[PDB]
Structure formats: structure tokens, C-alpha cells
Image (cartoon, rainbow over all chains, first blue to last red; front, side, top):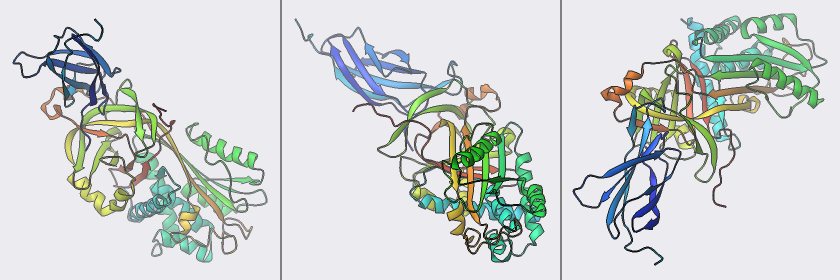
Length: 106
Length: 384
């Protein structure tokens, strides 16, 4: 009763090649948030990176204009020692978002 | 092990503590609750020891000890108090002090002072309750010295200044059988209600714990063993933020047994608020509601064995406790986190009001019953 999942994942600002994303913490201590992204439907594996657990935002760089992306956020929860490799992942939270074709200013 | 007289009195003490818990939970003014059954029972035992006529018999009637002899009640309760301040593991902290305060113009009898000291470790003090700066300073500094500064204040006022004041000051700090790491702490919002949130520090750890999630009744229950598994802290919490009333009504001796029988050994990721919770109750009006009507009445009280004062009555029964939630506990083998049974923990995220009990596993006696509704902290506010 209460899911281990981050919440309110959204794109705050977007550019043709970039996305600024934000989310709310899941229950339980988070050492890192693992952010995965890839083209929607495409059989290409997803790219991933981490941001410290003290953060609730991340920037996804090096994207293509006018392309649909699936963005997923997991939380990496330590079992006991916060600086240990023993951790379990939360359930994922994901959104689909198309990058703009052009920047707002010419 | 406990003798037959002490075992039946431990069972009656738990019944009495559940009854006070339910009556106090109905009082909408009360937020946190913290009762130690043996301290509540020893307070009635002191009334029986210092009383005569229906004042002492009503105290025995609440403990259902009308079949037992007078000295058997004091020996039985005396045995229970010693057994809990000895059988609980060395690393588990439990400080308790009991003091009877009478007015300046009162002489306590030698026999009452001797037996109250022998069975209940009761201390005695004479005080001018009307000089409230001096009276409060004496009560609060005694309670602070008893608890090593953990409970620095029993009360902010003495409401009734013309009788005896019984004060029980305690400090309990559960030392876990498997410690939490002191660095796995973060700041979170504790939801007192669906619209009131307070900023708290939370401590986190995952381990194998006896656990039960009732989807029908929308509650979770976990048992956290204390040092050497000689006692355990049981936490009962609704799935989401809600007034504890619905769960408190379900909670009985029989239902807690069914819930404990349904617990299974599972990987649980536990998050708890970290800090000291100071809970003080004047149990005078609640003890009257359970049978102790004469002792608390200025005209009908008969505390003549306590003092020849006459017209002396039980003006207050302070039950003051500092309960510390902390990471401290025993070390354990961390290789457990590489085993299959911990691949997917369930979460016990106590960010909203919960009920808790501390039980001695050797005798099955109830050490504490309470609820954490309002931890220490300021109301959170982001957008204004």
C-alpha cells in the first residue's frame, strides 16, 4: 500500500536537441535517479545516465529535432549503506515527448 | 520467568493500557499517545497502598485484583517493574522515575514511604504548588535529571494545587537488532493530515522483517526486533493518510494476535521519522472514567495511609515519556543483500500517523502502546 515509484515526471523546457525534465521523489532514500531515453518504438537500445538523489531535475542532451522520445526515471535505493553498490531499483515512471523541429528564436 | 501473580497482573495491565489508549484517542484534543502499562498499573498500586475504604478498593477493582491479597498486588506489580527494567537488553535504554509530590504542610507516613519505595521505587517531595515558578522548576528539573535531559518538561502548569501529584518520568530508546546506517537520513514531509505536512528527518534501511499488508483493511503491520530479540517494536499504519480512529477501533488483543499470526518473513524497506517525541499525559480524568472516582475527588478521597492530612486527594497522575527514534542498533552481516529473498523489497514508508507497541518476547508483556500523530517540526510550505 503505496508504490515505490517517482511521480509527476514532466518536460519543463525543450529545445530541438535537448529536454529539461523534472519529477517528485518516490518513498524511501534515493542515492541516484537513473534516467533512460530512446526513440519511441525504435528497436535501438535506450541510453541511460544518473543524477544524484538530492536532485529532482535533469537535462537530456544530444537529441534529434522533431523526434518522439520515451523518457523513463527510476530511483536507485540503497539497502543499507548509502555509499555501497548494493541497491534495488524502484518501479519506472515514463512519458513520451516529441522534440521541437526549430528553436523559438531564429 | 514471571510468577503467576505477576503474569496475571501483566495481562490486566495491558488490558488497562488498551482501555486508556482508546479513551484518550476519542479525546480529540490529544495528538500523540504513549502509555507504559506497568507504570499505569503501579500508579493504581500506589493509590491502593496509600488508600483506605472505597478509595483503595476502587484501585484494586481497576487491576481486577480483588481476588488477590493486598500485599500480593504490591509484590506482583513490584516483580513486574523490576523484570522490565532488567530483562530488556543492555543496549536498549529505559529510564523510569516515580515521585509523589505533596503540599508543604504534609508529612508522609514512614510505613507508606517504606513500602512505596520497596515495591514501586517511589520518591517523595513536599512542594508549594501555588508558587508555580518554583513548583514547575522542581517537577521539570527532577524529570529532566531522571531522563538525562531527554524529557526536559513534564507540564507547563499545575492545574490542581490542593492535593498529591504523582509524576512518572520516562525515556525509552529502542536499540534495533539490525541497525540503520547513520548516513541514510534525508528530509521529508510527514503528513499529519491530508492538508497539514511537517518537515522531519527520516531514517531508512532494508532487511528481513515479519510483515503483513492487508489489502482489504488497507493497513500494513511490521515487527522490528530490538537488541538480541528480547523485545520488538510493532508498527501498524493505514495505507494512506487518514485519522487513526478506523484502525484503533479494529485494534484489540484478539485482532493483534491474528495480525501477528499472519505476518511472514519478507524484505521490507523501512522509513521512519527520526528524533525525540515528548508525550505527557495527566491520566487523572481518564483513570476516573475507568473506576477510580473516589481518589480523584477532594471530598470523597481517603489517602490516610499516605498521610494523616485528610482531604488529600489524587490531583494528578502525570505519565511523561521521551521516546527516541534513532538509527542506533547492533551490527549485522551485509552479505544478506546479495541473497535472492531481498531482490524486491516491499515498502513501509511511515510518512503519516501510525500506531506502535513495544512487546517483551520473553514474557509476552506489553511495554508500550502509543501512536505518532505529530512529530517535532515546523509546518511545510512551498507555494504561498
